Image (tube, one colour):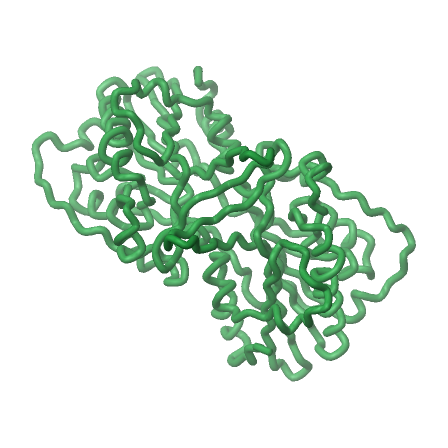
Length: 231
Length: 232
């Protein structure tokens, strides 16, 4: 039956600061996986070259472009953050591949999401390893007649999907191997910067169900147990 | 620094092989991304039996992402097999496997029973005029420009698991003639009560339309085994 090949395959991409899974239908990442360590955050502002590039290893039919974003009113929000990888120039520049980028409401990118990223980095002082998994969500809302719909904008000629929400899963690895799970969801909206990050914790099961992804079985295969944080 | 993928890679491609088809599955929509069949003429059994299994949830999909009959029940949508049951009358198992809900998408009943069924019949009918008829079928989620000027993707989700309701469906027939040359017909119908009397040809679309919108690639793989396809 596969005489003429399979119409689509798993699109994994390994970069020097992350690995990701790419969804060609959304023209966006499904999840991005980083590993934070305290020494990987130390660095200077030496070269400061920061231009988002389009991912040439994604077919043109399904590759977001800078044009898709300009004039959209949406910031180019890097899922794997540049500041996570100061120690290496290449690790920083790879976060500027648009394959690592999703349309974010500017206020969110600059304030509440950015504060979530700095919290994640701040945890690198108290844990020997901070694994970070970031990605989009397209959450349905129930109308008053009982019917539910997924609705999200697409921007640019390439119809790049604007997520309704974003998730960030933190696998906090202490020195002794104990592991702490913190799962955050924020709407793709102007989130009040003064609400504490604790309020955005959600059970990891709700992210797994809504994302089509699975975390807890792969964690708790090598963790044995895990402390599920729900502030 | 240890290694990046120490915990799991959260997403894995999900290919399923059945005796009647190959499919790849998308857990977010709780539906298939595409289904690939090969219709061959004696693979339609003119003299045979009629054993229709029940629709069954695919237990090889994690329950977080598995469509159930409860999800369709009361939705008002038919359980539309992407790989049609009538395509595999040769074997009882090859047809039983089309009733795995991983092969199923919510279809407007009128579409599934009248216009999309006729398209399935028409594709079976070209098994008489071609060596092999390869059929790839899948959902589409097409955006619309609204009154504010911005384009939006909007679709219903049904049942407790929020199974995605495609806005459109596509079907791509790879027609392999005797001279081994391949003609390509690709159709698109809206998930809607399509007028039965409209000629199927009017639903033909350029394959690039499908590839662009579905996120899939067909032409490069055809030229990878053939050398040249013909018109749209």
